[PDB]
Image (cartoon, one colour):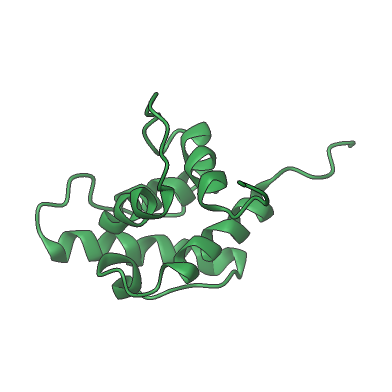
Amino acid sequence: GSSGSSGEEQIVTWLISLGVLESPKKTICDPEEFLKSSLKNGVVLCKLINRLMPGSVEKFCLDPQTEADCINNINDFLKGCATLQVEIFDPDDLYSGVNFSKVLSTLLAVNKATESGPSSG
């Protein structure tokens, strides 16, 4: 079992390692839901890119109490993703939860682009 790095886990640990997501000591068996729900709000994504690149999000919602706030976050993040030129997704696929296969990927790429390759010089 557990043969092949799907991605969910990679993202769960990736975000945290950076310092945008919480680091729950407990293990998450079903990261698929924990993720979708985590990114749902959108504030988690806005902070992510912000760390990846200096000045990615002008201003996002830290504690969105209403929908209009949650959606605003997601969208923002996208504004920064356009810089990496990686697959994007709709604010409904994540907020509502219709298609996650795209949300997970969109992030997977960004993570690969960020990874520091050439160091010398």
